[PDB]
Amino acid sequence: DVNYILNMDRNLPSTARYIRPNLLQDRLNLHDNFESLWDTITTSNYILARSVVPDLKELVSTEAQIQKMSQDLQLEALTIQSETQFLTGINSQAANDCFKTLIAAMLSQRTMSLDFVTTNYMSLISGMWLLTVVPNDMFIRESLVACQLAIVNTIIYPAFGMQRMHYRNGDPQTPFQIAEQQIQNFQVANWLHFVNNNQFRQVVIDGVLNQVLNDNIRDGHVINQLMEALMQLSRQQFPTMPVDYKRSIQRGILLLSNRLGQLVDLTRLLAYNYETLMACVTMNMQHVQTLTTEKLQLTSVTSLCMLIGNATVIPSPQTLFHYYNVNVNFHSNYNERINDAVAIITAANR
Amino acid sequence: QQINLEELMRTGDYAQITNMLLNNQPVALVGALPFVTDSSVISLIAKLDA
Amino acid sequence: MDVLYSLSKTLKDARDKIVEGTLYSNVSDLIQQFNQMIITMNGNEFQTGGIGNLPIRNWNFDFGLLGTTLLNLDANYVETARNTIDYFVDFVDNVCMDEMVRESQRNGIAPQSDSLIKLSGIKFKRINFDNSSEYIENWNLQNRRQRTGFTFHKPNIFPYSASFTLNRSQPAHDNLMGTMWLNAGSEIQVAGFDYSCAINAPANTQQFEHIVQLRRVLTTATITLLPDAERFSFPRVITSADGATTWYFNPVILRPNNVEIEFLLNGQIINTYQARFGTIIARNFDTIRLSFQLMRPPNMTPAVAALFPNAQPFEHHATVGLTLRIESAVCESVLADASETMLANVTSVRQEYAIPVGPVFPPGMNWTDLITNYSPSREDNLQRVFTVASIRSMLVK
Amino acid sequence: MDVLYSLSKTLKDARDKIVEGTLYSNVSDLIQQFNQMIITMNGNEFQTGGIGNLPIRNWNFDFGLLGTTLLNLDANYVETARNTIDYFVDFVDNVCMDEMVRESQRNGIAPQSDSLIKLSGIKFKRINFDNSSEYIENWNLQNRRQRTGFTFHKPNIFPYSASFTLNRSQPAHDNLMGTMWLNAGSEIQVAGFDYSCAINAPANTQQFEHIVQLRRVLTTATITLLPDAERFSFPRVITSADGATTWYFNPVILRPNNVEIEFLLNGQIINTYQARFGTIIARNFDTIRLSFQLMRPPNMTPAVAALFPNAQPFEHHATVGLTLRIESAVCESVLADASETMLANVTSVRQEYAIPVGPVFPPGMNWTDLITNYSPSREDNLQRVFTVASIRSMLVK
Amino acid sequence: MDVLYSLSKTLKDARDKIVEGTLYSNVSDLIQQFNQMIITMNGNEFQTGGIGNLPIRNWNFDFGLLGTTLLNLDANYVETARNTIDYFVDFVDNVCMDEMVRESQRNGIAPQSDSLIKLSGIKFKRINFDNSSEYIENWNLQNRRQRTGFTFHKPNIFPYSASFTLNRSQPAHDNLMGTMWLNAGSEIQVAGFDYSCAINAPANTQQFEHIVQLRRVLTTATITLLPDAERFSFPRVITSADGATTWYFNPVILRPNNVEIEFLLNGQIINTYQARFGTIIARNFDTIRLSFQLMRPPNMTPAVAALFPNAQPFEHHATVGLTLRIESAVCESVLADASETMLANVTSVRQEYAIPVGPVFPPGMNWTDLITNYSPSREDNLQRVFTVASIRSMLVK
Amino acid sequence: MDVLYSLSKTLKDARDKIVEGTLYSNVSDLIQQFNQMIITMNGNEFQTGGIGNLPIRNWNFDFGLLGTTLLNLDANYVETARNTIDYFVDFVDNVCMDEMVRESQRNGIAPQSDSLIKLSGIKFKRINFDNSSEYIENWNLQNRRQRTGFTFHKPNIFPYSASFTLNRSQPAHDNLMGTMWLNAGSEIQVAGFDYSCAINAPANTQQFEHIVQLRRVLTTATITLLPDAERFSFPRVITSADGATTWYFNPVILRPNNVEIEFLLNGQIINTYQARFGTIIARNFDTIRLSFQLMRPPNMTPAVAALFPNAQPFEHHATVGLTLRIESAVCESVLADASETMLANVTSVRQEYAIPVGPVFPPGMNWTDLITNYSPSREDNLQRVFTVASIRSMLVK
Ligand SMILES: [Zn+2]
């Protein structure tokens, strides 16, 4: 990884000696029954992650943006349910949280939900961002349920004029999807298959035994996904219901688009970071439906989004190691005690 | 041969230079640079420049 | 259809560029394309076969993606991949074959099989890619209705025809005059004979002519034209025109006089060559006309004079001939030639699976019968069927 | 081995895509692959030659890499590159040639030379890439124990054989009956002659037959079958079977009667054609059987009647024949054909360097001898050697 | 020039990889290259035609670049693109043709047309890329001075030549001895005849020899050599050397004795084969020498003895012959062959547009005339013109 | 397939190393492997039989693991284990047999039965282990396409052939000269007889020769060669060649003179022995040629002289002979021999279950018919079928 410099400085006597780390894999498949404990690991592995994920920098002044926002937003225009789209603030934070939170989730192979807020449509738009990237694969089926339908209904379908039959779902297999088979606008149509796929391409065996469910080069920094997520948006501007509606909605959409030049940057960021950090994980990691969630307020999400500039941050060298080191030890302990354990038990029998 | 300095301090130097210097091989460098004038011939015979 | 194509170049450029070693970066652009496929497929269900001796096989899809992670490729990576490819190969084979047998009069151009009809569906179009395979290249250009074109070595434009025409004959067949020929594939041999050696002919010269009408225009043809027809330079006992008896042909060969070859297009002379033997170019033609003469030698040594008496019996039969071979040419319509295996592939798959004779193609895909009555329906079906054979040969030979 | 391949496509796609001007982002994916190589190599020593008149040149590695910057390429960039390529070219040439001469009874399918044996090493595998060259494509599919396959225009399946068989003869050789033929390359010509014109034969018909056993099965063959054997249609003076004297053959040609061609596979008829001249398909066969008859003409004009008396001397010898040519076919084993230069490349390199006759191949890589006794060892060595010739021709012709 | 090349592979790899449904990323590396072009072009204006019947059309550029709508292209994307391609196609065609007609003695290796001369300009070099098309591949390697090389099937190396040489003759032409032959394309047939059947010849053997000098060296040639010259195995009435009368040739064929074929290079024997019929390799030669003998049969059955009396008249003329065919070979110079359409393309474009005869090429691009006097100027012009024809055939067939 | 193997060595090394007593530690490594199996199986469902008289049987899996607890093994431990083994034994038997009957032309190498086809599945590969059983050992090495090899005692390479060839005969069969032989299994006996005792033969010596062409090459053969053919040393009444009558053979034996045995490979002499009786080594050959002579005794006691008169009747027939036996050899192809039960196992299972004749093997798995036409398909099927028989014999004899 070019960006990182390597060099040697001290020599080594033929006296040099170390002790094998011993990093056998799982040995114990807890992935298929000991839910209670996985939840506890995930949690752990998760916090661990946040501790690492670099804090962001150079953001757009909270005030400035939200202000051009009101100009664009046309907030108080009849609609009764005001001041629910602006509890967005504390972004100088929300983004940092939303950011960290997102990574660990992934790394730690955790699964979560969404402090969702139906009315606040914007908050939804951004949702579409989320699925555009984060492999829904690791999102308890349900929180995805709400999210999508909320999009699907209070959006697309009617403002796009299509199914004015809003949508009736009981419990098929992926409501977000199916929408595809019956949408007449390619742009819209690609989003659908890609999103309902991007299954977090769960297949990898690198640097010697490190199944770390990977992710699309595409996403990575081919990014386009974003460019396409936008282009599809660029032609959602039309009739059906009251005026203060399209006006408000589309205007918000545009804020995603313009910013899109930058939104790109986001993709790259994560792409790298996850793709980097990960490298130093010994513990394997099978995707599992944790028993516990993790609340992610579209609030923050939305912030991160239109609120990131030409910032650029990455894992401090020292930081990275520290990470390796830990998992390492831990492993060593697990494996070791295992041996210590077994040994006894077997003896215990004869 | 050559090696853009601008790209060097950018790239991070791959000991490419480090090696050549160590091993002594005819080479060149390029870009903005601080010159330094000397006189007392001596300096030269002594080959200070190396 | 175009869909189909991809499926292969996908696999080829796959079973080829993916191996124990290489860098990810060389396939990054590829890997993607691949996955994209798996997705579109998974969930869908298919059915191939059911006709003649062809087995019926059902296929389902539910496969994992590909590690877009790694830097280099480790052996293990391949094997887990090759296992997935082999199911698609064995698939396509069955897909091709199934659509390589069905024919259709009305619309003999579009897809037939339940397998392919489903592919032309819109939801799969998300797979097209790299159409540089000469055949598909031309398949498209024809949809957009534009100028196509293929390349052939020793093309197969002439339906087999071996016969004669007696311009002067009598019951005893002891003083004949006429021509005999063999048109087959890319070659024509024609001989003009005059038992009397033009003894009573004006200027002691007998004129001959051989016209061959191609069923399709050939352009940019490189042709070898040589004097003499070796095939008709030896003694023969031939059946009479009415099949009631047999005549004797005892040729002695003289150089063809005033040779003129015309390559015509719609009745117009496009190229004309006068007595030029060797390599000649015919740039665009649907007809070849060979005119040549037998001129009685004005001066003869005794040995020669003895062969040509003033009165019958005529025992040595003066013969002049020409040989013409089309080495290469371009045709806007698919044809069989001496290098491509398309005709053989289609014919072979049909024979192996005991496919019943259909309404379009002659029994056994007989080339002579096909080219003799090369109707629009036969050509559209042939092109569809040849294009599929070419898609199949990218993976299965 | 596969290793080797890369080395070239690397250089080709290199000496090709690296020109003064082009935009970098067209070679980004390429450049990489390249460097990767240099690395793996540097620090290694090789040696080629040592046999016959083949020089023993030594090689070492120690090279710098390539910039990655520059929107477009400046002349200077190329020249500093071309200089590095030329050392690899002149290298590979010597590598190919060195492994293109050695043969091994045992494992004639494995690497031989000190040069290559070292390449199959694991530490070099990090260089593999883009295996789409028809030959390597098939090299892999075989190493995995699977179904191979190649393409040939006018394949070379028949070892040269020109002879005759007298089924009825006598010292004077004045009333013979039998067949004579020429099997060579992709062609067969066979004639059946009966000096008596079946005068005393049952139904006045003489049956003939010619069987040719291929050393390898051919599939998907496009074949031209024509009546008559021009090669045996002229007067000849031939040596007797025992070489003690010479006989006279004075043919007169009649149409072959009841022509039947069978393409058999392991004794089973796979394809059969009755009197069908022109283009026919033989989809899978290891044997060709041509049966044809001479039927005495039941009705004869005086001129014909005069050739066939009731009693000897028989001065005009009734002859019927067939000509069969395999235009194209597929074979699971490598073969020489009329278009590929493989055999010629291998034979030429060995001749130029005065390579001594080895234990596997016949002197001079003689094709007839090779195909006549096409043992498994000769085939494995031939395939190895043909695949190397094809790798070499990507860079050096 | 190389410039030109790109222009096409650009369009091909374009009209090919750009279709309704492929993922953007499969063309990312491509798209770029494309745009880059449009830029460099726009603004500059061109003139094509202005000779014979060739129209003078004026081309001007004013185009918008290419979008990038994400995730597989939408139909609309294509059509707006195809519209731009079609102007370039119709362009290049006119560009090729315009430079495919001009010839120049002095410097007939460089660009002639106002159209191309402008392209060699530096400001355009920025386009060149993917030089893998066999012809351009060799165009470059020659500009730097190195070992070029092309591949041909049934190469066209022999200018048409059909004649005879009487080594012993007399006015009556009743006891001749000599040879007759046909050299054409890739084939040679030669017969040696002795009316006396070597009755008074030392050891009753008459020696024959046929030498053919190639105008260019052929390397790596795969050759078929067969005994007998069928073309000269039948009765003929031929014109005398002085054209004053005609002689009679009545051959009877015997096996050629002591056959020796030598493939020489600059007078040195490179390959020699003694009586080896079938497939032989000639690795590097500029001359072929065929030596063969007629040996009077020492033992003759009555029928044979009757053909060869001790005294004239000699009525059956003893003849021995050979047939040699070059199936494939490599030549450092461009040549016409039986598969490539280059000669036909160049000849066809010139004929269609009524291009006047120039100072370099023979009228009608006549192959025999061209190869007979294959001067350096004709070769440089031929190569330029063949390379352009090959660039054109990537898009227009 | 390899899968299958394990299943057994698992059970063998199981029903063997697991008994009332021993220490855990000796099986620790084993126990594991075992369990691992049960797991992979459980849940899955199978089906065997259905063809001919073979019963159809379904099997399910749901078994407990093994106490990895205990120190030593108590009787009770075994019995609870043996009960589980017996279900697998009775299983495998049915699995083997089911795949030991089906044959297949196209792909006669890969699995056939619904039972095995399911095993080659990836999810079961988690069971392979200890492949030291000579047969599987070679099964693998062949997949990786490498040099195989088996060991045989009195191999069965010669199809049964018992006949004679009369080089000199007459209706009365009172003065014959020729050879008679018996080629069968690993033995050859051949006798040369001359009723005239070479009375009128040049040097009073009659030459004989016997050539035997193996269908497969044998390497590292230990051979016994002895003078005399006991089988042809006694009086016989034999049928004439045309079956119309019977002749009398009354031999008297003389030592074979100038005995020369040649073991050839592709026409080349690899080993040659001149009059060497006893044990000789033939290291690599596909043909054996035995040449020997009968030399009339130059000096004869009265009793001997009386047997060989100067004139007929010839009542004592001089005979010389040789006996050759291949004691052991290695072959790259499976063969029947005098020690292995493979052929007998396969033949026996098919006979017991009344398996119908298939498309590959001759009726009754007849060895002579099989080895006479030992096609690639028969060999691949034979090897598959022999390897399965060997897997089965590890548990069931
Ligand atoms: Zn040819």
Image (cartoon, coloured by chain):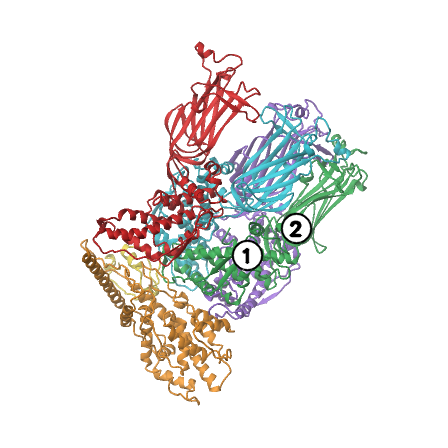
Chain colours: A orange, B yellow, C green, D cyan, E purple, F red
Distance in Å between CA atoms under marks 1 and 2: 28 Å
Give the percent coordinates (x, y) of residue E61.
55, 68
Label 1 packing within 10 angstroms: few (<14), some (14-19), many (20+):
few
Quadrant of the rendered image containing residue D39: bottom left
How many numbered badges does the structure rendering display?
2
Residue F15 shown left or right of residue E106 in the figure: left
Q: Amino acid at mark 2?
A: Asp
Q: Does F268 appear above or below D386?
A: above
- For disc 1, the marked residue is C50
Give the percent coordinates (x, y) of residue D214.
53, 40
Q: Does A135 appear above or below C300?
A: below
Protein chain holding label 2: C
- Ligand 1 is found in the corner quadrant, namely top right
Q: Secondary structure at mark 2?
A: helix
The residue furthest top is F302
Q: Earlier in the sequence, mark 1 or mark 2?
A: 1
Residue C303 shown left or right of residue D272 in the figure: right
- Tag on residue F45? none
Tell us which disc is closer to us: 1 or 2.
1
- Tag on residue C369? 2
Q: D81 and C171: which one is in front?
A: C171
Residue D358 showing in the rendered view: no
Label 2 packing within 10 angstroms: few (<14), some (14-19), many (20+):
some
Looking at the figure, which quarter contains the N terminus of chain C? bottom right
Residue F174 showing in the rendered view: yes
